[PDB]
Each structure stands twice: as structure tokens, then as C-alpha cells.
Image (cartoon, rainbow, N blue to C red; front, top):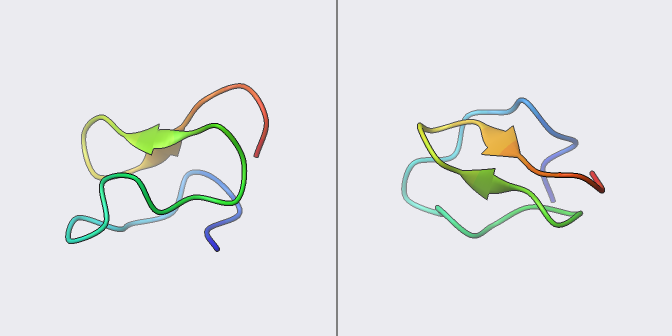
Length: 31
């Protein structure tokens, strides 16, 4: 799982916390 601010792309919903790849980077309020 991404630790935030990590590149994903293929996985727009693949993040440890409640963050998403709104632009390719995990951005939320948990990770």
C-alpha cells in the first residue's frame, strides 16, 4: 500500500489510508 504522495496511476484507489490518486498521487486524510 502507498504511504501517500506516491505514484499509482493503474491503481487510482490503491492506498493504505483514505487517499486517492486524484492526479496520480495518493491524496487523502489518513495515509
